Amino acid sequence: SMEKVFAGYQARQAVLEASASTNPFAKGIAWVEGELVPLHEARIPLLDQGFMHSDLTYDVPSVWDGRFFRLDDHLSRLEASCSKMRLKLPLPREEVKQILVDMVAKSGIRDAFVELIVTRGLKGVRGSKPEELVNNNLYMFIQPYVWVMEPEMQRTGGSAIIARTVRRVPPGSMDPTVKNLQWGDLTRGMFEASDRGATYPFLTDGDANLTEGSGFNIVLVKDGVLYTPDRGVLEGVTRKSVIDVARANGIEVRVEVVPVELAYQCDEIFMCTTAGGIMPITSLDGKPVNDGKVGPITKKIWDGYWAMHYDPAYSFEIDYE
Amino acid sequence: SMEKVFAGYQARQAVLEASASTNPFAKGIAWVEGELVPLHEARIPLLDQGFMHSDLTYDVPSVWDGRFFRLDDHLSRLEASCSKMRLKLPLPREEVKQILVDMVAKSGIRDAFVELIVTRGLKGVRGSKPEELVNNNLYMFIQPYVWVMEPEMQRTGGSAIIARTVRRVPPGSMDPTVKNLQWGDLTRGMFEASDRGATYPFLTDGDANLTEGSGFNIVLVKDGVLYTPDRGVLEGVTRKSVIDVARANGIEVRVEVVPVELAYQCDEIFMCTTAGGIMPITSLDGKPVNDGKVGPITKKIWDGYWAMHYDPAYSFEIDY
Amino acid sequence: SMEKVFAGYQARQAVLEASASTNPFAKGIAWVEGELVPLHEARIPLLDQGFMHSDLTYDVPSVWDGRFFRLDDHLSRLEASCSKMRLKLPLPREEVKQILVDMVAKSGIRDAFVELIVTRGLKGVRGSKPEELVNNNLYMFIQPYVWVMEPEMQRTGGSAIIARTVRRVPPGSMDPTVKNLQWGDLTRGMFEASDRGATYPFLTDGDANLTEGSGFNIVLVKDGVLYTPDRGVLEGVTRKSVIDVARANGIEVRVEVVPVELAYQCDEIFMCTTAGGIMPITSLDGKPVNDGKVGPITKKIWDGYWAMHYDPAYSFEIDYE
Amino acid sequence: SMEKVFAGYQARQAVLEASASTNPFAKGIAWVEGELVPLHEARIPLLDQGFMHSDLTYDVPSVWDGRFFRLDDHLSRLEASCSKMRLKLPLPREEVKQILVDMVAKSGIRDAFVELIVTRGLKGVRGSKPEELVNNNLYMFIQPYVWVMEPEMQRTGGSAIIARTVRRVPPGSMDPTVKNLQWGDLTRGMFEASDRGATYPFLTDGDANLTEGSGFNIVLVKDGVLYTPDRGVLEGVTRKSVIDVARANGIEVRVEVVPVELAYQCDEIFMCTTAGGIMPITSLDGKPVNDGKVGPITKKIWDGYWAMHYDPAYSFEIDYE
Ligand SMILES: [Cl-]
Ligand SMILES: [Cl-]
Ligand SMILES: [Cl-]
Ligand SMILES: [Cl-]
Ligand SMILES: [Cl-]
Ligand SMILES: [Cl-]
Ligand SMILES: [Cl-]
Ligand SMILES: [Cl-]
Ligand SMILES: [Cl-]
Ligand SMILES: [Cl-]
Ligand SMILES: [Cl-]
Ligand SMILES: [Cl-]
Ligand SMILES: [Cl-]
Ligand SMILES: [Cl-]
Ligand SMILES: [Cl-]
Ligand SMILES: [Cl-]
Ligand SMILES: [Cl-]
Ligand SMILES: [Cl-]
Ligand SMILES: [Cl-]
Ligand SMILES: [Cl-]
Ligand SMILES: [Cl-]
Ligand SMILES: [Cl-]
Ligand SMILES: [Cl-]
Ligand SMILES: [Cl-]
Ligand SMILES: [Cl-]
Ligand SMILES: [Cl-]
Ligand code: NA
């Protein structure tokens, strides 16, 4: 149930904040050039191309109730993203896995936002031969779980708008399956949502089709069928878990081109991302979605998603010692 | 004169190199939270939104022969970029000017690449009211002049391609008049150019029109008339200087939609940006541009652009 | 003041409507291969490439109160469209205008919809040399004045929507300054407007900018300044007349890129085309434009536009004997 | 065996030519308002919206060696196209099939190009209720088989270019799965190919991906795998047959987004459409495709495609009495 899941998070959260006075990693821990530092003290070289030209890729696994969730899927996506950008994970994947879990155990964080960043390094791409672009930089940090939609808002649903002043960066400019931090369009959508009195922007592809929002995939529900865009979006691990939950309940999920018009004619809407999970949308463009309540299929997806966090096929326990 | 301008630069480079053993700022100086540090030692907070989400704007003025070139145009464009992104220059504009001048003077660099970065700060835009987004961060650094085209290549021109695996980010996603560091498409084009045996990628808008390249504007020349794209590109200060020079010489500049086909049927091609100046392109898609030599109008713009660096209306001397 | 012009047309309508029994051309007259036939009896070859592949351009001048309005501008734009499409007006422009006034004369129509069509001919472009594509076909007809907005609606303003299920054909696909009959996107927009309970669709370029609608240009007014898109649209003769009226009245004109958001924050909206003239819009997306009344700048352009039809510099009288 | 197919076609061509003196339908037959006329005498009303605004859909089945090829697949696609455009086939599809067979038998054409056109009718969409737009018009005609690539050129393959002055109309403007005659972009591409010394234009989607050409789908072959675009194109019946032949031969076909770069790195290229069949491309942008010869996998698809014309699951024999 939703109340039991959030009550456990609130308990573990309070325990974490009580440890902050004696554990300098309780607010987060970062890995910078082989050194573990408190997150809010972490610094990176100004000349790092991940800053100078956002020449990087990244990925965000999570920890819930002391259990890493689908970590191997995120590490595999990071490696695929690195290869698409001609980057290379600077450490063996097995060592990265050991460092990540050790950082979580040192922080004591039971519900964690985990981020890995692989940047081009100190040498820019311009005027460089491929041989001198191999010293890629790696940054990792753990921090308390981040909510794109706060737990209280998940009980009643959120408000969204179809963005009309900004469209998603097309794949011909930037591959949206390569997770990146070049959030120019998404930051614009967030400003438009604030100007229009809503919280979440839904960005189109400029061809009257839905893509994704500012840090989440979009799923529409109409007549017992789930619809989510197949192109122009990140292939989210949460979205993959949504498909797993729907298949277990005999619910069809159509991963295809989704017209904007369907968002106005569907029964339920919810957002999905690692930093938040399953987040219902009960208002669109100032009007309620159907009856303005969290739909029944959304709760089924919501309940199943968090149940997967204790399935040993998708999670493993962390030894905090 | 190309040889005269470059010979002066190489001579000043020897002076800078000889000073490096006793000046820790000779390789660059950075301004971080009110502190001046050697550029290669400068560090920024990991949680800065300029890194966490590239939530920033920036601008790049330059120094040549100890003269700041068109600094007030770059400072004004940075302020216009900040307002468009709901950022604000964290220091008064005049105070920023004196810091940059003092930074250049401390470094001893006579030909300088100067960069100013304004990021959102330590708090992200997501789930935030406008009041908690006013603590923007400022980063500035001086570094030796950066060449998108090396001086020796400018004498003969470079090789370019029309990018076919990537197109420019449309203005409906990111305003290209707001200078930003989200170079996803530009970095892809640089890889495609390397894959195809050329140096400079020319990105289209996907609608079969030219836009800009990986850090430079594009100007085509046909029958004595300059053509440069009017939308989907940065309004470069170098491009504005090109128009200034062509204005003084009676050369018509057409800032309009430029179709891709014109790049294959023009007489001269050259790029322009602060990090390099006027850079001729004598080869396109593996084929020569006209006669494969640097064109006469390009040389006219070239000579006029560098003479502008000693015009008091566009520059001022730095007291080292 | 609308009444004088409308009553003139309404009274001239009765003279034409009462002459329907006697006049075989009161409902229209067409020019097909050198012969003149009643409009609703005209026929074209099935193999004409103007039908087989919409391989044509066209233009619509008009007659008002027995005065051809800016006919030479429409003829020049037609010749420009032909050259851009590698077509050629199959008769000297001088013979075309003489044939045109003769057709209006025999029809007796005082307020007429005139349409010229130049098609590729009977031979298709596919697998053909340039020399085999020179026999272009010409089709011309006169028709009673067509209103994209009824005169009664023009006094109160109409309802419009920003199309969300369709966007305008980009110039890189089809040159919108070459007037064509490939209305696939405009027809979809008209269906969307009917679906959403409005009359007129406003199509975007997919990049959150305004373009044009189904057969008209769009003009926005805010703080006494006219705004109309500068690309991706037809350079309409009515729009050029709107700008001309603005020149004579000291109005600032901004022919530039108009973002979609300006339509939701402007003071007045009106559309313009030869088939209807100046056509106000007082409702957008189900909400009133400003105060929902025909704004003062629109009424100013409206009165000036129809006064040009009696200006000898822009019109000339037809001799009906 | 390309000779076996082409020689049989030439023998039937000689028989049809000798009958042209006595048969007025040997050059084609058209169905216009229930009347059968010689194709080159067929006329349509000028005011038909299929001409006035290209407000129509169409489809092209074919006859080979006296056998209709996949006719019901074309009729089903025609019905799906009509429904998407809010049109309706003006006759029962079984009667339409009976009429088509009767026209082919009456013409004596053994290898035929068959075209069916459904237009909006005489009343335009602009300012109309759904009731007044139900009188759709139907045009059908038979004519000798049309070759987008001549049989002799199919032996050595043709030359193509990636169009750089034009891009395909995006689906947000016009649905490419709805076969239409609004060939504005395709005609421009055909002119660019002629300007650049090539025969066939390959149009991109504007996002550095391949779509289709001027009346054909595009298939790339690399390392034994077939690639063809999954969006922005017509879902061709010939393309469907290509997938059928490749599946019967254990050859993988990937219907997915195809980057432009793959066209410059692949082993074989061929086009496919009803009017011509499998058409190899051995030159791209003035350079040979691999060795410049018709590839082995292309010939395998070529042989299987024509063998399908005698498979009872994809063809049926016409009784010419
Ligand atoms: Cl609490
Ligand atoms: Cl994202
Ligand atoms: Cl986030
Ligand atoms: Cl299905
Ligand atoms: Cl649906
Ligand atoms: Cl376990
Ligand atoms: Cl354990
Ligand atoms: Cl000097
Ligand atoms: Cl003229
Ligand atoms: Cl033909
Ligand atoms: Cl269509
Ligand atoms: Cl849009
Ligand atoms: Cl109309
Ligand atoms: Cl019109
Ligand atoms: Cl009279
Ligand atoms: Cl043979
Ligand atoms: Cl009409
Ligand atoms: Cl027989
Ligand atoms: Cl029926
Ligand atoms: Cl070429
Ligand atoms: Cl699609
Ligand atoms: Cl298919
Ligand atoms: Cl590839
Ligand atoms: Cl069957
Ligand atoms: Cl069958
Ligand atoms: Cl048979
Ligand atoms: Na959008």
Image: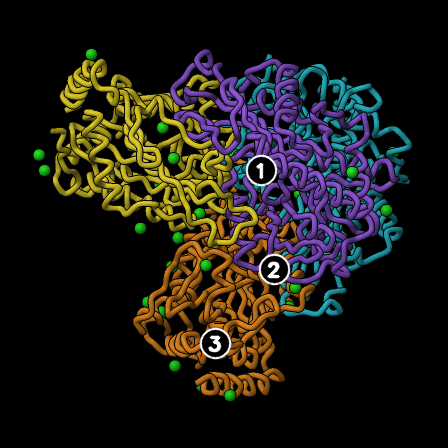
Chain colours: A yellow, B purple, C cyan, D orange
Q: What amino acid is at disc 1?
A: Asp
Q: Are marks 1 and 2 on the same chain?
A: yes
- Left-right relation of C212 to D260: right
* Residue at (40% x, 66% y) in the render: D226
The residue shown at (51%, 25%) is B37
Would residue C193 be seen by someone viewing this image from the given angle? Answer: no
Q: Is residue D41 visible?
A: yes
> Quick one: D147 or D304, which is closer to the camera?
D304
Does label 1 point to a residue whose CB lies under 8 Å from ligand 12? Answer: yes
Q: Residue beneath label 2, please? A: C52
On residue D105, the disc is: 3
Amino acid under label 3?
Ala
Q: Identify the disc placed on residue D240.
A: none
Q: Position of residue A60 (x, y in %)?
A: 31, 35
State which chain disc 2 sits on: C
- Give the quadrant of residue D302: bottom left
Alpha-carbon span between mark 1 and mark 3: 49 Å
Residue D10 position (above or below residue A194): below
Q: Nearer the viewer, mark 1 or mark 2?
A: 1
Q: Amino acid at mark 2?
A: Met
Could you confirm whether marks 2 and 3 are on the same chain? no
Q: Secondary structure at mark 2?
A: helix
Q: Which residue is mark 1?
A: C205
Label 3: how many residues lie within 10 Å, few (<14), some (14-19) or many (20+)?
A: some
Quadrant of the snapshot with the C terminus of chain A: top left
